[PDB]
Length: 139
Length: 139
Image 1 (cartoon, rainbow over the protein chains, first blue to last red):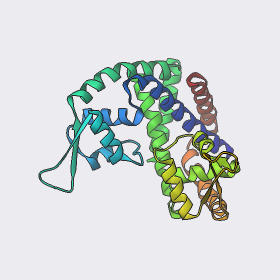
Image 2: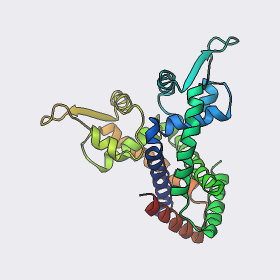
Image 3: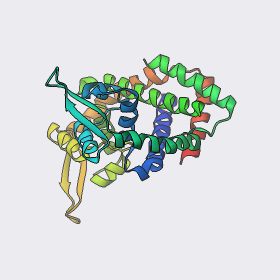
Image 4: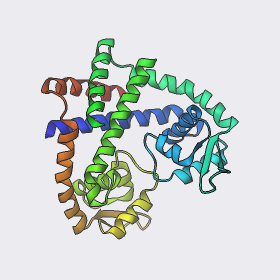
């Protein structure tokens, strides 16, 4: 009902304020949350496939191939055809992108503190329980 | 720290499971959350501008103009140049899109119940308080 609808709305609003505030925080590095996400994904995993990257993206945009090409010319990522399967593209961080991650992690750390630090320790425990209960229900 | 980072992660994960589950729910109507969003925005407001629509989108995709053209050929929305300002495009729902909203609202109502109804009434009140506290902090 209106209680369920009000809850869906509150969770989206908080999520959207968090992306807005993260984008503000990483602004200086000429990247947005979407490019930042790719850099985080590609640092953890090694040289993965385009498909693996799309799968590992928590949220996939409506222009991945275009968006990666932009990152390719910018010098953050490098793409190459897999010598085994010619219809597959492997993607990985360049030295510059590796260095860009290091520099952005400092602003990201500050982002999490300044934006996810408003609750008391008691409230954090309550919020954690409730959000994990919600995950189990949805998957 | 790790508490702040774990909280950011939990809120994103729940949000992403909600879009996944909504897309599954509205699948039959040949639309995704992004097209559904536009239909909801355009039903509430009347004939708005492309800019107004982009602003009123809680989350704006990386291909609005392309994505609206797709909805234009599909017959959900209609676009026209404003006779006052020629460099401005006005957008609005067609009869089909108006009818599509009616039919999707039934599945959306079921989506909210099946996905945002897992908490007790006591928990709903606690979750509401915590999420509103988070909004005030972020804006």
